[PDB]
Length: 129
Length: 123
Ligand SMILES: [Cl-]
Ligand SMILES: [Rb+]
Ligand SMILES: [Rb+]
Image 1 (cartoon, rainbow over the protein chains, first blue to last red):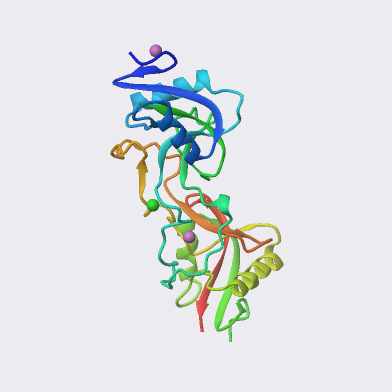
Image 2: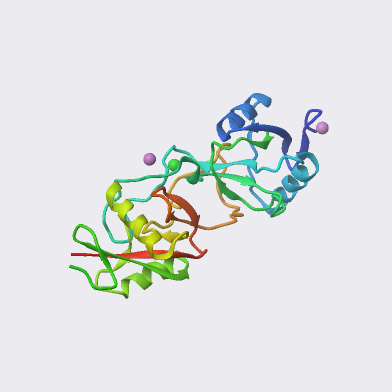
């Protein structure tokens, strides 16, 4: 059934938020919206369709990405041990925002494609319980 | 000492190229320009500075491949709801590191895309 405000799809409840937050504030925010709440996880094409549809009709005029729950867990700028010449990787000089280890959907690709983006960005999202 | 078409800097020879190639083709190409050739790697701030300066003096405003590939593919990607990662819908499969001729900051770009690049070899 799902609570007023949430929409149902094969056993789960979803709710889009046109709120701008970092991946971490979003995920935490989602946990506070429902028991067992998290940023939306997409485990099938049918579910991906259902999410794209929800985003299309509810998150507009934001010119941003839409947070999904898939990301690299740690805070590393990367997970590469050596350069192509075999030498070890020590020195590193990343622009904070150039390390894109979080995923978000975008209007351009019909909110059906996962784009690598900086977790520090402040984008809208969708929660799922 | 280095070949006349290359530029030396602390026991290493460097050379930028204009023909755009995806990361894989650039690296491989480098291996064919001189024994032990590969895409440039940065072990220090001064070395990177030298390479940036060279790239700019050579081609001006542009972007060049660095010797780092599939940088986040080995990271641990997972759903915050702890669901098994099975269905995939990636816009891009892998990212590679490059730098722009104006500064030594590391930036990211899909490995399948194209860019200019710098090759390098030791002694
Ligand atoms: Cl990780
Ligand atoms: Rb409902
Ligand atoms: Rb790091």
